[PDB]
Amino acid sequence: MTPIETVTAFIAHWNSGDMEAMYDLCAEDVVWHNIPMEPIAGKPAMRAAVEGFMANVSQCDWQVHAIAANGATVLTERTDGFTFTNGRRATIRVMGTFECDAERRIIAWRDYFDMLEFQREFAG
Amino acid sequence: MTPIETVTAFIAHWNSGDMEAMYDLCAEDVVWHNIPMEPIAGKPAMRAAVEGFMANVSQCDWQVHAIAANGATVLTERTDGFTFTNGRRATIRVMGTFECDAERRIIAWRDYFDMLEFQREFAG
């Protein structure tokens, strides 16, 4: 896949719940950084952090409004929707930068959003 | 001027303090939206908001880490530095989406960041 296709597919896997296909697009040394929080270094740590983040989440519906690339660096503007375990839904407005390597695996993922918007929806 | 050249110049004007050149790159009905805040609609409201935001700011130093365009849309990953009246400096991590018309007038500017990171640095 091209860099833009890789990020599009990554988002599609979050949306379908195919988490193994999602991890397969990431490098072993991937850094996942939600900007207001501590970065997560490496695929094993990513797996553990995802498990925690998704504990009360049944479905994702992340919508890409804009995507653009400069070589291997792909930028996005999105609305990330979630359905929680009880069926309530929420959205968080986010922009993200993805860096790919030469084999088009994701080596860095940095998401930018308001921590207050996040805390409101993920509390309780 | 291409969309990417237009946005690059726009950021350069923030960095030089040439605010009139900055306004000149925008459409009359430009929307400026710091995502955690109310959008600012139109050039007159932009001028007023800028005057307020910059009251205690002596200099801007905004660094673009990544920039990518897809037609009329330009996406950015930045660290926006500020020097306040007493010489204190601060930085805020931000991603921004810019939209242009076909004549490359800036019609929308949406910046994504953590309100807590902003409030920390701009309080007092």
Image (cartoon, coloured by chain):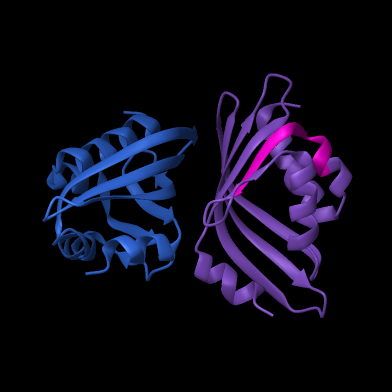
Chain colours: A purple, B blue
Spot the residue most to the top. Answer: A102
Is B34 placed left or right of A76 in the picture?
Answer: left
**Residue B85, percent from left and from top:** 11, 56
Q: Quadrant of residue B79?
A: top left
Q: Give the number of callouts.
A: 0
Which residue is nearer to you in this view: A54 or A59?
A: A54
Which residue is nearer to you in this view: A93 or B29?
A: A93
- Work out whether B74 lies above or below B56: above
Is A101 placed left or right of A16 in the picture?
Answer: left
Asked if the magenta segment contains residue B54, the reply would be: no
Is B46 placed left or right of B87 in the picture?
Answer: right
**Residue A44, percent from left and from top:** 79, 43
Q: Main secondary structure of the magenta part?
A: strand
Which residue is nearer to you in this view: B16 or B9?
A: B16
Which residue is nearer to you in this view: A92 or B71?
A: A92
Give the residue at x 79% y 52%.
A48
Give the residue at x 76% y 71%.
A83
**Residue A82, percent from left and from top:** 72, 67
Give the residue at x 23% y 60%.
B46
Give the residue at x 76% y 27%.
A1
Q: Which residues are magenta?
A: A22-33
Is A47 placed left or right of B27 in the picture?
Answer: right
Which quadrant does the C terminus of chain B fall into? bottom left
Q: Quadrant of residue B113?
A: bottom left
Which quadrant does the N terminus of chain B fall into? top left
**Residue A7, percent from left and from top:** 69, 39
